[PDB]
Amino acid sequence: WGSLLQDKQQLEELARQAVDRALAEGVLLRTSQEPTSSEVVSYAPFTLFPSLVPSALLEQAYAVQMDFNLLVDAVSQNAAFLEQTLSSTIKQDDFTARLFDIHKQVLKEGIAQTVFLGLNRSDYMFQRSSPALKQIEINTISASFGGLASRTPAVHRHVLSVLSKTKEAGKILSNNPSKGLALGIAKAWELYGSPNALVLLIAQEKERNIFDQRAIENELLARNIHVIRRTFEDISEKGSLDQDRRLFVDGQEIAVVYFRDGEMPRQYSLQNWEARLLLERSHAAKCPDIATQLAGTKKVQQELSRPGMLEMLLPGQPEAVARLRATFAGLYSLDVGEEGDQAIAEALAAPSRFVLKPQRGNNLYGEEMVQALKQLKDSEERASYILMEKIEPEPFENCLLRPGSPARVVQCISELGIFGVYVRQEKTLVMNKHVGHLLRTKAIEGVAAGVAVLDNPYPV
Amino acid sequence: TNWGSLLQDKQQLEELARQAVDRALAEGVLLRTSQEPTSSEVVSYAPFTLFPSLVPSALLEQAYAVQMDFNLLVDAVSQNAAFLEQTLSSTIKQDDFTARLFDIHKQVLKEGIAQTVFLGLNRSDYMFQRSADGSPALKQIEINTISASFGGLASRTPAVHRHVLSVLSKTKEAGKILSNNPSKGLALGIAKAWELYGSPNALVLLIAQEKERNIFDQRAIENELLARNIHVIRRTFEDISEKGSLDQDRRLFVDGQEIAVVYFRDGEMPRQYSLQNWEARLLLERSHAAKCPDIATQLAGTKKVQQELSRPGMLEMLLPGQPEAVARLRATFAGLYSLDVGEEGDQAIAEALAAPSRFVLKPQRNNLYGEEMVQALKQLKDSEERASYILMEKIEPEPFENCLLRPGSPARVVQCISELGIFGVYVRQEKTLVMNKHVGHLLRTKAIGVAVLDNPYPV
């Protein structure tokens, strides 16, 4: 479809068509100027065209989501695994220490909730081996863009239709993760067993991605389930527990706490840490619970790759273990010791093969990674980082539409996300599924730079 | 209302307003800002009401029931050269805008009309007058025969009002909001004209200025056409001057592509035309393409034609043997008065000078009330420019309370009045009427500032 654009004039004309359709379809962010206000909005950056994705790789990513849901839930329930895995990390990293301290406090007091759920997103890249599916990470707190991802297929159908490619417009895959994500919260709300109780959505006041979050709220409203949006500071001021640890905000009972904040250390303060502890101690279901946020950390991801580790967490499930392990790339501990020393030495000698990732645009490549490794080698801070195999997908051409940037065709690579939803009542899994996908695409330079834009996986 | 009376403090109102605005944005109820009217990189919501305003079912039904009569009336006017010439003979001597529209109309009649396909997308607007008995009566403000607006955004607002009522657990009331999709019906009129034109590869040409806040409303019509494999190009009058060309059969080409339908979303006001833009308007009118509207149909929507249509026996002359249609049309007419030279115009001027509260002064080309109207009438009485104005009965609906949401303005409950619009679509091949229908409604509400989008809640 690229060949049909004669020059920059035709490209800019098609880009204008795409942008106006994206806005009409609700593919929206607040402005960076006014992240607290909907009095002006922009479009969420997205690709002019849907990017080609081999059907086998998309199928493989879908086929392992229920395994990842079981694995994260198994990790969240294994106090010894979490403590052994994170012991060195919590000594160095204040953020992980504070999350772990809340986990320890609620384990000590006893878990108040009987309803557990996860809304997550497992992210992959296509490694040049033929392409192979390899996991970047799994996002177990504030799994984003399921709302906007439900709105972009119509935009790509519009762009292909403008070019009279109506057969190709029809091959774009329908995608509605926001319905599935909402249905996970709705199931947890039903199991909590208070018809008048609310869903509490924790979000900071500065939230450019509010429309993505409102999509989940709109789906719950359609099912007569009401959401209140509150900050951690609002919970510090107004939240409290009754004698049975039921959570009340503004006199209203809370059934489900849905986090869309609390993933990064700068989002906290003393009062916000106090609020996170109050929420975790409550009888409300948490999405995620504190142990499940810990299950999504880089150090857990690295330790899950150790020989025999998956078998220990998922006993007697060889097919599930095989599907999970197939997605694992090289993951290396940088902890003090000979093994961490070898990984540092390998990355100093061949920096193009590795990425340095803090326990958390913070990843380091090339010369910046080499400078950081020289500083980390004789620092106990080395426990707060992992090294990973650099995944280099085959670049391809697309046009990344972002406000303030002229429409230009550039070399790109993608990240494929699968949205997972599971719900457990006590020890019993009642829901475990995939609910849709997210393709995001970034310009290369080879290191991906700029923020990833929304895309759709065109099946080939 | 059951919903309105739950909002007792400013914090409650502001919280519900935030819910409304976020849902409106998600539903594509969008408008460019006044300061960035050429760019879609930063936009906002089209102003709208927090709640749907109460509208008597009988008045909505009456407005729908007269639309097909208005479509016949405007089409009949457009085809009656003698009626247009007699009606506007004094107007064209004084008003440059009417003179230039009329001159194109005359040049095309003299050359011969090239198109064989005709259509109108229009919007007939009403207010609810307090009648003698105290019961409201439906009275026409005007009919918009060029660039009939907001049928795209009106297709998107019902979901917003359902959301607001659902937040308040008023799900029965959310269910009673009327479904409304004028965007689809308006596009289907263009699609019918495109089918009758008979060129599978011909385009719809949408004429629009580069400075266009209401682009999203316009795109809704384009989206509906694209769903039916009909393609739109947006061009300015300046683009048509540069690139528009006719073949020996007066087929219109832009960038080598044939044009089946010219859909005007510009050209309703004099300030939109340079001399080059008037040349472009003539080129388009001379072409074989269907025009929405044709120049005669734009003239059919003007204030002077509106007033002359109220003369005794005039409807009967334009719509012979149609007594039930004539009665439905005439029922909606308020007082409309010529200000042309002569005793009658003198009588209207004297009545308004003496009792200004009863009247509004309206230009043919900016409506004047009270003291401002009196000063203007003193200046117009001994001026030939009186031919460029009509006097109209002042319609004062019963005020009611609602909350008008506008970007950058605080949420406030204020006294309001509404205008109810009905969208009309008709398509004709030569003498054969192929489509004639209503396709939806538009309720707009204003503080007693800008009219905001609303929905008529049936009572």
Image (cartoon, coloured by chain):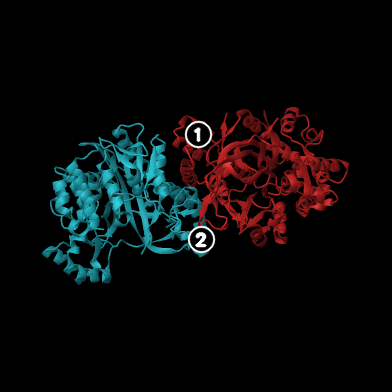
Chain colours: A red, B cyan
* Left/right of residue B29 with respect to residue B60 in the rendered view: right
The Cα atoms of the two marked residues, 1 and 2, are separated by 50 Å
Q: In the image, is residue B346 above or below residue A197? A: below
Q: Position of residue B303 (x, y in %)?
A: 23, 56
Q: Which residue is mark 1?
A: A3
| Amino acid beneath label 2 | Glu
Q: In the image, is residue A44 above or below residue A313? A: below
Comparing labels 1 and 2, the label whose residue is closer to the camera: 1
Q: Is residue B416 visible?
A: yes
**Quarter holding residue B128:** bottom left
Residue farthest along the right direction in this orientation: A338
- Given residues B186 and A371, the one toward you in this image is A371
Q: In the image, is residue A460 above or below residue A88? A: above
- Given residues A295 and B39, the one toward you in this image is B39
Q: Position of residue B294 (x, y in %)?
A: 26, 45
Write down the chain letter for disc 2.
B
Residue drawn at the location 46% of the way across and 32% of the way down: A165
Q: Which residue is mark 2?
A: B14
Q: Position of residue B67 (x, y in %)?
A: 27, 46
| Amino acid beneath label 1 | Ser
